[PDB]
Image: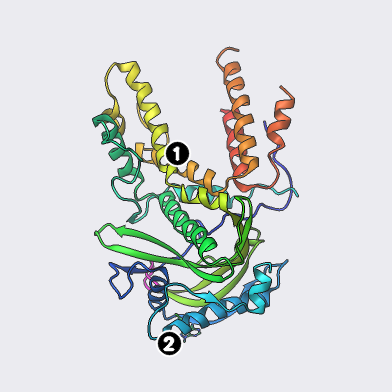
Amino acid sequence: PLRLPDGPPCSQRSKFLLMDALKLSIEDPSHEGEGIPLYDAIKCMRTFFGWKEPNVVKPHEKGINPNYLLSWKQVLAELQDIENEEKIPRTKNMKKTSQLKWALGEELRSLASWIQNEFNKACELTDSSWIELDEIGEDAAPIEHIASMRRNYFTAEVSHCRATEYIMKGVYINTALLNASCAAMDDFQLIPMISKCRTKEGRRKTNLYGFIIKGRSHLRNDTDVVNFVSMEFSLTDPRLEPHKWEKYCVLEVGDMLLRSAIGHVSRPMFLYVRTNGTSKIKMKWGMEMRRCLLQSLQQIESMIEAESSVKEKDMTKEFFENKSPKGVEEGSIGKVCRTLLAKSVFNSLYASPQLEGFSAESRKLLLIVQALRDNLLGGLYEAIEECLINDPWVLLNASWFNSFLTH
Ligand SMILES: Cn1ncc2c(NCc3ccc(Cl)cc3)ncnc21
């Protein structure tokens, strides 16, 4: 089996919160400015009244925590500035304050259990649909009948999937930043983190996860970096899994009244803050996250076009309806679709050279081991294990890979 590294537990490294995010939402919006992110965010902000004086509750151990506190206070100050203006601007350029100049820039780890938990959360369904019925595909021509049937069965099973929400979240924020990176090169622009869903009842909703502030972005090449500060709401207390949050300063910024299985309960609302950066090429990929839906669909269609060659008839219906196989090992056809999707999305969210190395070399050891398995290599192990350092996503697949070696 593979040897995973020893060390302190791995920490979160995505460009935004995943299972820990928190949404401020408005239903079927129709205010003077429905569709301009700044107007949407403010209207989501004013939905919430439990704000309170913020303080640091889990410090970033390598950054200057007074500057993170001041930056969040500045956001509320400048948002409150917009409140006082007669009209609402289309965008907001933050004052180039001391805290923002500092925050915008102007070793072995062990597998922690939070990343498997993220992956499990990415496979669940939500109350809300995140994509339209004809979202998947780029076809110039109308789709033939069999393709259409598969595309609609598959969309039924993943439209509400949590991984799909990560897709649209990511596409939104990456489009917003990439565009801002070009239209406001010298500004510290305030960029809402938005997404849009439809409820089980049919209502269009708008969600605010928090805010980005981008720094100077004269991105001349694909690999040039624009730094940014992320500020994300959450009900997750950082003191439970502090190792998850090494890269973050976390503030407590309000209290929130929630329906629960015990009735109404008041929980603190937190605000996860970190500095971070991205590049033109990374943001272009982030805008492409819908292809995760298409790539997941194809892996599904592959299993069907396989079964269909063996039975001389189209097995699309009998596969999705679960009518030779005798069940579905994940539980249901639906969980197989969402599982494939979640893996593809997390490949995107945690894209790394260590993942591209591990993916190639481990497939080599895979075909060798199951060749040996049903019929009865030391440098290869070093290639694969040269990828096992500190990435939570690489390490978790390596953990998964070792299960396959036992069964
Ligand atoms: C009692 N109370 N109410 C609000 C509040 C707060 N946040 C200010 C705020 C809230 C929303 C916006 Cl769009 C701008 C600024 N901070 C501390 N106490 C507070």
Q: Is mark 1 within 8 Å of ligand 1?
A: no
Q: In screen coordinates, is 216 left or right of 332?
A: right
Task: Please tell me which of labels 2 and 1 falls first in the chain.
Answer: 2
Reply above or below: 75 against 243.
below
State the residue in front, 263 or 121: 121
Q: Dominant secondary structure of the magenta stretch?
A: loop
Q: Is residue 154 visible?
A: yes
Q: Quadrant of residue 297?
A: top left
Q: Quadrant of residue 242?
A: bottom right
State the residue in front, 29 or 232: 29
Q: Quadrant of the N terminus?
A: top right
Reply above or below: 14 against 67.
above
Q: Give, as a three-letter code, the residue at label 1.
A: Leu
Q: Tell me what residue is drawn at x 66 percent, y 73 percent.
A: 101
Reply above or below: 398 against 231.
above
Magenta region: which residues?
A: 258-264
How far across and down, in percent of the image, does residue 238 sit?
A: 59, 65
Q: Quadrant of residue 277?
A: bottom right
Mark 2 neighbour class, 10 Å CA radius: few under 14, some 14 to 19, many 20 or more? few
Q: Tell me what residue is drawn at x 57 percent, y 53 percent.
A: 280
Q: In screen coordinates, is 223 left or right of 344?
A: right
Q: Tell me what residue is drawn at x 59 percent, y 25 percent.
A: 366
Name the secondary structure under disc 1: helix
Q: In screen coordinates, is 179 left or right of 217?
A: left
Gap in angstroms between the C-alphas marked 2 and 1: 48 Å
Reply above or below: 206 against 356.
below
Q: Give, as a three-letter code, the residue at label 2.
A: Asn
- Looking at the rendered structure, the number of numbered marks drawn on it comes to 2
Q: Quadrant of the C terminus?
A: top right
How far across and down, in percent of the image, does residue 318 sit?
A: 27, 28
Please name the residue that numbered disc 2 is placed on. 84
Please name the residue that numbered disc 1 is placed on. 340
